[PDB]
């Protein structure tokens, strides 16, 4: 089907399970996909597979969210502007889980890395990409949340803190961009990272819906890809 | 009165604003207060005023949440252990507001600093002080939140993200320390940097209540001062 024909969508963390699947799904539904990640070799392989499966070859760009500066993000936007006239969607799928252990045991360097990737670099990249999103007829900006971004639970430490921060950033952005951008979060749920869990392919309907026109009047919300 | 007699309470950001008022109020109600802050001159001043009002002189310790490492926080806790048998309360009042302006205009350096102070260093200091809090009969740990930690609103940028993170941290801690610590947030609301708004003295009732016995086994909650 053709939901995303003539839509240009950037996917971060594009080499991991959910990111790869989202990139492939968007391409299957007609999108021009841009892959972002740390490792050129993994991105090239993802792009090659998408091309084989869809006839569409995504371009890719390198950014390491753990260490990037705002200037690096601005340079990435500049590279995008040479080849693309707008972004219709940005899916922020990059992330670090970090330690799953009590607060008394959480490693402080790991905590700082989780916050730096999930919150600070995600913010910096969003800022760099807002002008391109504003050029869409209806840009859609999607962050990745978690159940522990809405109710903190024991052992989830930095990840929980970072996903609450993500919900808050999303809400601030949605308020600022009423009638200009749609800004929402997806909680993928527990995914096949065991036969008890759903696979990334199973949770794709919500990923598609948030990028297609059916969700144009939806902003400021957090959605569960499962339940 | 004597609500806080024989309670040892550590207050961060004690050298000004709400922190200074909370330290002075707790001491007036009988607490043994420990002042934490970045500025020695100001901490000495506050300690001197408290002594004038109570006849008991609080100790102070220097910690700068913008710059401190985990090891610095551990060393601070070692210094407290030399002087004190437990902590009955920790009130995290230190924070940075940062930029109030649209997300497209937020300065990324200021954003990083708001997150470092309000989230990372607040976490690292909490971690260092947990063993002391567990030595209380009923330790109470209190974070500072905001209305924009529950509903994000335009222009509040890093502060909002950091106060959302603060609510999440509080909730994780409250879940881990069920039946062991009281862990809650206070949203002070709009207070003194203006003549129209409440002063820090006016919002103290909630700050006292969370440290006194009448709030025992209230945990995992966020309160408006309000």
Image (cartoon, coloured by chain):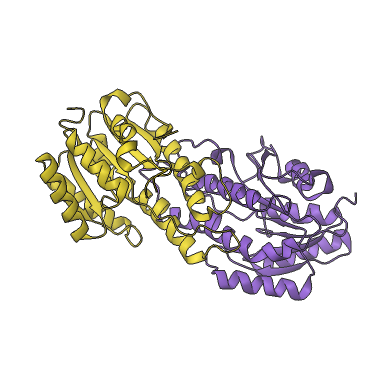
Chain colours: A yellow, B purple
Residue in front for this viewpoint, A55 or B80: A55
**In which quarter of the view is residue A176 placed?**
top left
- Which x, y percent locates residue B127? 61, 63
Q: Is residue A47 left or right of residue A207?
A: left
Residue A225's quadrant in the figure? top left
- Residue drawn at 26 percent across, 50 percent down: A14
Q: Which residue corresponds to the image point at 41% horizontal and 52% vertical from the top-left?
A: A118
Q: Is residue A44 above or below residue B44?
A: above
Q: Position of residue A81 (x, y in %)?
A: 16, 45
- The quadrant of the rendering that contains the N terminus of chain A is top left
Please state if B163 lies on the left or on the right of A71 as rendered.
Answer: right
> Vertical placement of A212 versus B116: above or below?
above
B7 horizontally vs B77: left or right: right
Q: Where does residue B104 sit, x and y in percent of width and height? A: 35, 43
Residue B77 seen in the current view: yes
Residue A65: where, in percent of width, then height? 33, 57
User: Can residue A57 be seen from the camera position used here?
Assistant: no
């Amino acid at each position: 089907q053709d939901l995303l024909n003539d839509r240009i969508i950037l996917v971060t963390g594009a080499s991991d399970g959910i990111g790869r699947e989202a990139a492939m799904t968007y391409a299957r539904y007609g999108a021009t996909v841009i892959l972002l990640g740390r490792n050129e070799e993994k991105l090239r392989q993802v792009a090659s597979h998408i091309n084989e499966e869809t006839g569409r070859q995504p371009q890719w760009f390198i950014l390491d969210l753990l260490t990037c500066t705002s200037e690096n993000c601005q340079q990435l936007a500049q590279r995008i502007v040479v080849n693309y006239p707008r972004l219709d969607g940005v899916l922020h799928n990059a992330g670090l889980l970090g330690d799953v252990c009590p607060m008394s045991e959480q490693n402080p360097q790991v905590w700082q890395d989780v916050m730096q990737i999930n919150v600070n670099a995600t913010f910096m990249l969003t800022q760099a990409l807002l002008p391109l999103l504003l050029k869409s007829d209806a840009g859609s900006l999607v962050f990745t949340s978690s159940s522990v971004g809405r109710q903190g639970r024991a052992n989830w430490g930095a990840y929980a803190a970072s996903k609450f921060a993500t919900e808050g950033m999303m809400q601030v952005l949605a308020d600022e961009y009423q009638q200009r951008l749609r800004v929402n979060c997806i909680n993928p749920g527990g995914t096949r990272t065991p036969q008890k869990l759903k696979t990334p392919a199973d949770i794709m309907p919500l990923y598609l819906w948030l990028m297609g026109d059916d969700s144009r009047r939806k902003t400021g919300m957090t959605f569960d890809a499962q339940p």
